[PDB]
Length: 129
Image (cartoon, rainbow, N blue to C red; front, side, top):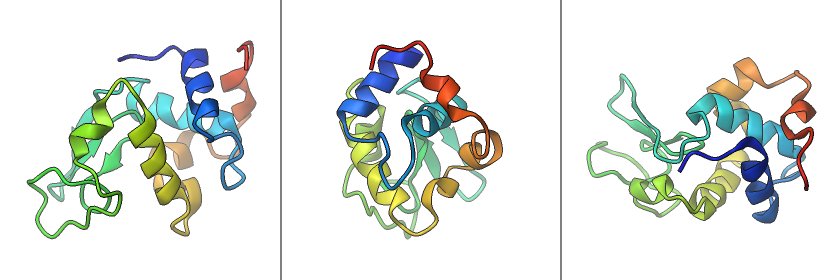
């Protein structure tokens, strides 16, 4: 599913991401835009052999099992395919674990480089929330 901006903001709010670990909703919407273009089916392979999955591009070395990333840890206890669903629940629940891991949203490279320190409120402007 390719979400609209406000549609995704509302879904993320319902699943408890607004101000989760102090990160306002716009941060999460911004991260999703630049990680996946709001597409739940996005995948991208990395040089280390791992793959990133879903709307928040969650990595198979640490967080989910895809059956082809040797010595990976599956910390979210989910198959990586679950992160591609039109239902974002699995992605959100795993993202909550990642953002609590010590480095906050810096775990998402696109957030660090394109969202951090910007007016992220713009990403939820106009939306009925």
